[PDB]
Image (cartoon, coloured by chain):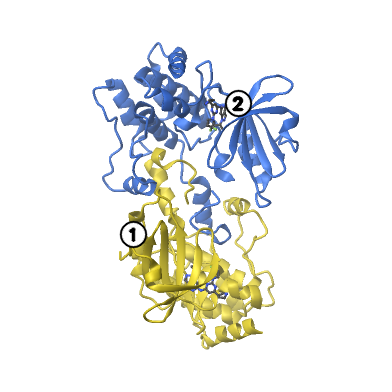
Chain colours: A blue, B yellow
Amino acid sequence: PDIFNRDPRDHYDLLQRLGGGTYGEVFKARDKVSGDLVALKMVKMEPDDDVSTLQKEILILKTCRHANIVAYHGSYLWLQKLWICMEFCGAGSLQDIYQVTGSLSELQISYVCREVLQGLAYLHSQKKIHRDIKGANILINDAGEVRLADFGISAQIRLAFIGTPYWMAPEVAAVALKGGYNELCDIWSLGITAIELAELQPPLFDVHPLRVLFLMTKSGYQPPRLKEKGKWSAAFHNFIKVTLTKSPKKRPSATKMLSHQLVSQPGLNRGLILDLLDKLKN
Amino acid sequence: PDIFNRDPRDHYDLLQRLGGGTYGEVFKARDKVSGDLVALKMVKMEPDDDVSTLQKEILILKTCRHANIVAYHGSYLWLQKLWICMEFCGAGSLQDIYQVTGSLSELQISYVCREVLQGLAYLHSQKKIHRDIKGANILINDAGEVRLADFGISAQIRLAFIGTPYWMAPEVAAVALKGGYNELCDIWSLGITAIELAELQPPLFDVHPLRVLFLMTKSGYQPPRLKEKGKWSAAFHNFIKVTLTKSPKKRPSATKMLSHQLVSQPGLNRGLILDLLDKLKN
Ligand SMILES: CC(C)n1ncc2cnc(Nc3cc([C@@H]4CCNC4)nc(N4CCC(F)(F)C4)n3)cc21
Ligand SMILES: CC(C)n1ncc2cnc(Nc3cc([C@@H]4CCNC4)nc(N4CCC(F)(F)C4)n3)cc21
């Protein structure tokens, strides 16, 4: 709730443009005073967007004290532009990384999964839902540590609804806000992410999005699998099988998944990502 | 399913640009052969959109034989542009109209409601849902007749989802397709539309969309009312009250609403809209 009505250039020095997503650009910046490096996610706004509607989402991201959640430092509104300031992760997303390094090993994937689960267990304990688990939203810093990127803010500045809000029935409004989601949907997304990291794509990546969603509603839908059976351990395959449980009633929770063989095995540490980063330099 | 891979300029002559919505422009055109006038809704496409995913929606709009549903004549795909060709309504939408004429009388509103209900009863009998009932989507032709504008096509070419499809759990995919909607949500939208026609705005029009939806989820939410009590009959107020029933379980169906005093009263005919159109000329 500390949204500063200041120019973030008073506190930070912009260094370079990391890129830009569906909305907004991301900058690498340095704090004037501490010299520390931060990430600034910028989002352009109209005189139509109201900022106070975001205050609940920014509360969510601010009151998140976990090692596997990227750190929030404040927000800045200035001249119709919104800036979210966060702890900087030098290596970027797993997707930035595997697009150069090629597929991850089972050990690297296992460690990432464990770390992601740790952050999810936390989030779900605070009754929050990430909603967008995927390789592009898992950040790696230069110490090989793993951070879930920001959530719940990007999808509310979705000027797109199947309908028009002022004319929406209450039941429609409810679904348009919640998305029918539940916490265990993060667990499914994690399973797909593990395949993504293993195969450089999520399943059905070469197929139109709408068709993919259609197919998931058919009576006899079959959850995706690892393509190459021989390449991966029985434990990995089972991890995939149980995270991609079709019914959300039978799908294991984050803390339950943390007890899984694949992520509770010894020897999982950031060293695994460190030689992944070394591979980046080769 | 008769989507022509031709240039619609072979069959139709473009005359003038009626305007443009969130996506695409609308043209007034003339059929070369019959001389009849049509409306052409154009929508620009990428090499990312797949046309066959639309074939189910175009089937919906094609197999609709009702007097209160705007008539579909065919589709055209050519050079990454999609054209939907429909019966032309000369006066445009009720919104195009009331923005010049000012508020509608209770009699004009009643006749519009009846006609809209007739189209809805039909749609719901074919187990279809309009999803976007509002003044901008109720068309008036030069004979004062009433036509529901196209539906289910506009909201699927919503490249916006709270999440990423390939990583979505099945339960999430289901809600992202259906929208949790049910047919009776059209009835709510009709009620809001009746206020819109009466007051030139839907309720809470000057309030941020997200806030409006939030409010509809609160324990003690109160459905909107006609602002000026004295201006409208007891029948009109009751029509508002029952269409804006909060619980979709207690909300009346289209055919039930057709038995309502306000829309079953004698003397409701297109003559009412005809002097509305005369007012347009003054
Ligand atoms: C997701 C983003 C809003 N965000 N949030 C917190 C956060 C913390 N650190 C980074 N760090 C990085 C590092 C790198 C590495 C430099 C050399 N190439 C990769 N690239 C990127 N960008 C690649 C494409 C992008 F989405 F613009 C980001 N971000 C990004 C961060
Ligand atoms: C909703 C649209 C896709 N559609 N679908 C079927 C259809 C049949 N007839 C019209 N006719 C008209 C008439 C007029 C009147 C001329 C003089 N001004 C109003 N304006 C408009 N446009 C105003 C703003 C728009 F959305 F571009 C339309 N459309 C539009 C139609």
Q: Amino acid at mark 2?
A: Ala
| SS category of the residue bearing label 2 | loop
Residue B203 shows in the view: yes
Picture residue at 59% right of the left edge, 86% below the top: B275
- Amino acid carrying label 1: it is Lys
**To which chain does the residue with label 2 belong?**
A
Front residue of B244/A88: it is A88
**Is ligand 2 within 8 Å of the beta carbon of the residue shown at mark 1?**
no
Mark identifier at residue B56: 1
Q: Are marks 1 and 2 in contact (CB under 8 Å)?
A: no
Considering depth in this image, is B30 or B178 the residue closer to the camera? B30
Image spot of residue B61 (x, y percent): 38, 67
| A6 sits to left or right of B223 | right
Q: Quadrant of residue B30?
A: bottom left
* Left-right relation of B198 to B142: right
A25 with respect to B151 (left or right): right
Rendering coords of residue A202 (x, y %): 37, 35
Give the chain of mark 1.
Answer: B
Q: Quadrant of residue B216?
A: bottom right
Nearer-the-camera pick, A254 or A19? A19
Disc number for residue A71: 2
Residue B218 visible in the picture: no
Q: Nearer the viewer, residue A218 or B73?
A: B73
What is the secondary structure assignment of the residue under circle 1?
helix
Labels 1, 2: front one:
1
Residue A235 percent coordinates (x, y): 30, 21
**Residue A215, percent from left and from top:** 32, 47
Residues marked 1 and 2, same chain: no
